[PDB]
Length: 62
Length: 143
Image 1 (cartoon, rainbow over the protein chains, first blue to last red):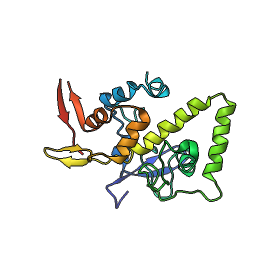
Image 2: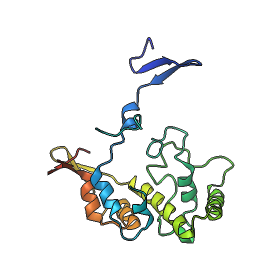
Image 3: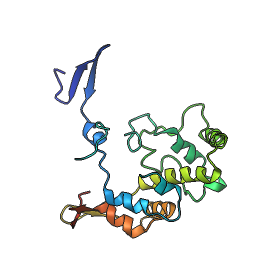
């Protein structure tokens, strides 16, 4: 965009789409700490909660 | 991304709202919910109600469908309880402290409910919200 430094345009199959850069970095971040998962996995009052759970992970890569 | 963020005139996934509208019900009182403007993960877009929809009647239909497909009532309470903990986890606030670090406020009401619901220690969790292994030395994280 001629008047913006915070947006970009991709020409996709059907048409052009202007995407606004604001909020892209925070939404993409998805890096769980291992320690926190161990706290949950070691439960003793809840059957289902440990049944769920068997460089840098991100929403985009996922 | 939708689980923890919403933009103007958008909601989180429907099940969270179906749960808040069903909050005053007797079986759901251990989940300890308020309305949708209470929780950080359901209040962001300013839209709490969809025109023409009773979120509570849809919860009745949702539970009935789980009953039809064999998710035993013991496991149904399982799912709703984890979702209530995700909702309470979202209102955990962090207060900045020396040397770019943080800590929870003393006796924190959202965190106390989160730990009760999940059945974990309070202090073990409170520690590892604000701290991280570097590998073996323990180091504080920024807010």
